[PDB]
Image (tube, rainbow, N blue to C red):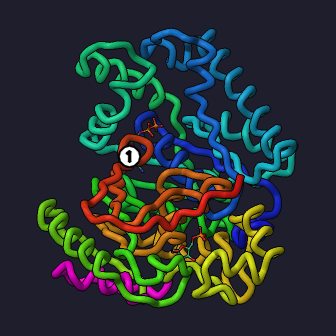
Amino acid sequence: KCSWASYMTNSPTLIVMIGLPARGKTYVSKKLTRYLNWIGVPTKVFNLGVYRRQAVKSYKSYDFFRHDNEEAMKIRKQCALVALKDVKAYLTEESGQIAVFDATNTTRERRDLILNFAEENSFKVFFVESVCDDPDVIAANILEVKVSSPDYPERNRENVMDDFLKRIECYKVTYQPLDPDSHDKDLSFIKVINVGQRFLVNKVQDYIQSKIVYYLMNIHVHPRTIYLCRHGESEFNLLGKIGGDSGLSVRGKQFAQALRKFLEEQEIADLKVWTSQLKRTIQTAESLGVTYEQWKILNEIDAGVCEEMTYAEIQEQYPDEFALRDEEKYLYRYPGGESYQDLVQRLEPVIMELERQGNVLVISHQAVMRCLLAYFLDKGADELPYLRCPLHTIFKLTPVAYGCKVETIKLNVEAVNTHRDKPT
Ligand SMILES: Nc1ncnc2c1ncn2[C@@H]1O[C@H](COP(=O)(O)OP(=O)(O)O)[C@@H](O)[C@H]1O
Ligand SMILES: O=P(O)(O)OC[C@H]1O[C@](O)(CO)[C@@H](O)[C@@H]1O
């Protein structure tokens, strides 16, 4: 029942973040967790800032982060111990597989505490250290996420900036970066340097660490927009037939023309356009006046022996299978075809190239687009096969703060509904 990636995960793993404040640790933690869950590895983030704010519930100044503030250090360490006990419960009672421990973890002593904890429980440990000393990057990071964060009340960014830079200075006093030449030569880790310009990778142990490294080395923080839509309405859509390779209806062609105008009105810089190899997506892109790329792996879910049938026909001919699919829509594999779980695996190179690229429009299909949207919007396997992705609607995805905003844009061309709810 588990995904391929989860099949390749054995002992539970602790991903341990390291770095000074405002180095993207929370951003990376959340994003890596979203990716790992989407590929089928149960993962949870443990944000030590959340624990500490819950414990302290006050607007502390940089004074709280001094290494010689004994009472603050005691509280901060207690928060780490509590979070680690929660990590242990997640990975041993709740069937978690990866815990992402999002804290500064800037001293050898604190990292030894985590390593000893992991050894007590036979967890593997992989560190992700973010290193950046460009003051323009740090200032931008502070303005982007720290000025309007729960650590601070309403007050001008100037004063918040001042306090947060002093906080950073407190951590610099005791910061011991990972050192692969001596102290840390046997630890497994990646240093992400200068916002992904440079990386140092040491002692990758296993499959999941290799995948984590590849992912982290191919993401970026440059602003851009991802657009997702389906092909224009197809002949088979009008007949309720699944799969196939039918062409656009005249109304799907009208949508394609409306999509051309939408793009001609947006003037999105350097927009890449990707389609599948199925005629209905190709014909949609042909109307746009742009060059585009056809990806075989964007083809719609394979319904196997059920290709080109209506749901009514499938239920009549295969009643037990049809009922099984309604009970387990994510995991059910069509005979001779695919499950949504298979489709997620097939789409992983799409996700990776979307991460590498800038502005992209993907013209695909109902099931494919559910999978892609679930990745960007952090939707689990229960929800993924039921996300609503109407024909003739564009989903505009904007990376925003720690996640992704979604706006739906319905173009003014009607279409049949192809969304089948789970019965009763
Ligand atoms: N490798 C990185 N290095 C530096 N900044 C990054 C990196 N990755 C993401 N960011 C930036 O970090 C900001 C978010 O910071 P945050 O995750 O809250 O920092 P931290 O948890 O280290 O205090 C965002 O502006 C994001 O663009
Ligand atoms: O998983 P569901 O809800 O049957 O949706 C997938 C189906 O949707 C369609 O894109 C449109 O009917 C079919 O080609 C495909 O088999």
Dot 1 crowding, Cα within 10 Å, few <14, some 14–19, many 20+: some
Q: Residue at x 50, y 55 (%)?
A: 191
126 vs 4, nearest the viewer = 4
Location of ligand 1 given as a quarter of the image: top left
Left or right of 132? Residue 98 is right
> Residue 89, image x and y in percent?
82, 38
- Whether residue 252 appears in magenta in the rendering, the answer is no
In this rendering, the answer to whether 242 lies above or below 141 is below
For disc 1, the marked residue is: 405
Left or right of 106? Residue 46 is right
Q: Residue at x 47, y 82 (%)?
A: 236
Left or right of 160? Residue 16 is right
Question: Does the image show residue 194?
Answer: no
In this rendering, the answer to whether 127 lies above or below 345 is above
Q: Residue at x 45, y 31 (%)?
A: 172
In this rendering, the answer to whether 332 lies above or below 164 is below
379 vs 65, nearest the viewer = 379
Left or right of 181? Residue 414 is left
Q: Residue at x 27, y 71 (%)?
A: 255
Q: Is mark 1 within 8 Å of ligand 1?
A: no
> Residue 295, image x and y in percent?
42, 85
- Whether residue 281 appears in magenta in the rendering, the answer is yes
What is the span of residues highlighted in magenta in the rendered image?
A: 278-298
Quadrant assignment, res 328: bottom right
